[PDB]
Length: 11
Length: 580
Image (cartoon, rainbow over all chains, first blue to last red):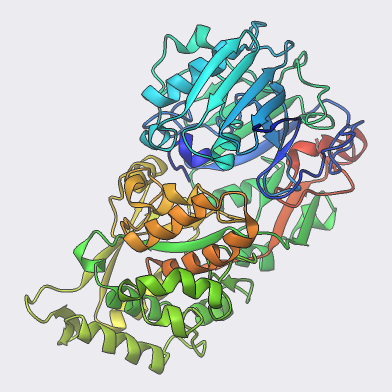
C-alpha cells in the first residue's frame, strides 16, 4: 500500500 | 472558512473499524504469553539487509525492520492506526497534514525518534531512493515545524498519497547520514521495530530476536502480537527439498502451493502420531493471481495475434485434471474475486469512459465478456489449436515443414521461457509440447535466485512467470505497474506504454477515495488489460492450505487479509508431546 513507491520488486 | 479535522485513525474508503474505544484488534489474544522460537523456510538466497537499495537480494523480513507513523489492521482493506504518530490534524481534501510524534518513540540504541528524523527520511527517499518515489511525490514537502510535529504538503489532493507516507519506514538520521540509500548493506542498519537481527550466515540463515524493552509493546496495535522470543529463517534452493525438510521437522510451518503434495504426500509416522496439523480454510477476499508475462517490447511478442495464439496453446483443463487433482481455478481478472472484476457486459457508465477511445481498443471490449480459453481436457483441443494456426498465419508466421517461420524473412518463431530453479514447474513440458505441435520452439532456462531477481528487474526475458498481488480496490499504486512514465519501476512486467491505460489510471487517481466512481473505472481498466493479452493467465485458489508442527496456539478469530502468524504464541503443553 505504497510499497511499490519505495522499493524494487522482489519474488 | 476551510474546515480542519483531527483524527487518531484513517481509512482509504469509508470509516475505520477501530475508530472508538480501541484496546486491541478482534483477531488477537491480548493475554498471549511471550517466549519460544518459530523456525520458517525461505527459497533462494539473500546477500544484504537493505530492502530499499537499487540492487541486491534482500533478506527475509528486511521490509519490517522499522516502525512507521501509522500501521494497518489485517481485517480491513486499508485502515491506519497510531504507531510512531499519536494523531494528525488535516485539511478536508487531505492536501496537508500535521502529524504529532509520540514523545516515548525510540530507536534500538535508546535515542528518540523526532520530527527531524521524518523530514530527513523523506529527503533520503527523494534523492537516493528508487526512481518512482521522486516522480510520485514531485511537488510534495515534509518539514519538521516543531520538535514532535511534522507537516506534509501535497501540490494536489491525494488522500492515498498521504496515507502511503504513513507506511514509510522512519530512519535514524544519526546512522543513515553515513550510508547511501541506493547501496546494499552487508550488516543490519540501526532500526526500531519489535524484532532485531541478532545473527546470520549470508545466503543460509537469518535470526531475529524479540526486543524485550520495545517502547511500543503496550500500544493497542501491538497488544497480543510479537509473542515469539526468536524467529529464524533457513534458506532452501528448491521447494522439493524444503517440503522433505518440513516433514522431517527441520522447520515448523509450511504454506502448501503444490497440489500433488497436498493430495498425496501428507502421510507417514508424523501425521499418524498427529505431530503435524493440516488446515484448509476458504478465503472470500481479494486473491493473488499467477500469470506469464509477454515482453511486448520484443519483436516475437509485439503482435496481439501472436500473444492470443500462444494463450490458446496453454491447456489449463488438461493440466488441472491430469496433474493437479482439479485443485485450481483459472485466473481471469486483475481485480480477482472483487466487485471491480469485469465479469458482466459493460454498463452505461463504463461506455461513457470507453467510447471516446474506441479507435484504440479491441472491438470485444464493447461486445463480449473476457474468458480465457477452455479445452475439452485431453491436450489435443482441435478447435483451440486450429484458431491458434489461423491467428499465426494472419500475423505472417506460417508452417515450412514442421517449423513455423516468418512469411517475409524465413526466421523461425522461437522464444525463451525464464524460470526460477526453486519453483515446482510440472506445467512447463506440457506447454512446450503443445507449442511444438504448432511449430513453435520454446527454450527453457532455469536460473538461480540472484539471476532471476536481476533479469526480472531489467525485463531481460521474452516470457517469465509473475504474481499479480491482490488489489481489493483500484489504488493509485496502479500507475507504478502500468502507466507510461513508470516503465522502469521494476513493476511493469510486459513493458506497456499505452495512452488508453494512462487515461483510465489518471481518472482513477482523480477519483481517489470515491467508491461509486471507482466501480466502473476499475471494470473498464480490467477490460483493457485482459483483452490486450499483455499476460497469459494461469491460476489461483481461494483457499489457504497450511500445515504446522503442533507447538502453537492461535486466537479464536483469523484476520481477513493475512494469515495472522504474528498473533500466534508458543504453547508449552502442546510442545511437550512432540519428539525432542
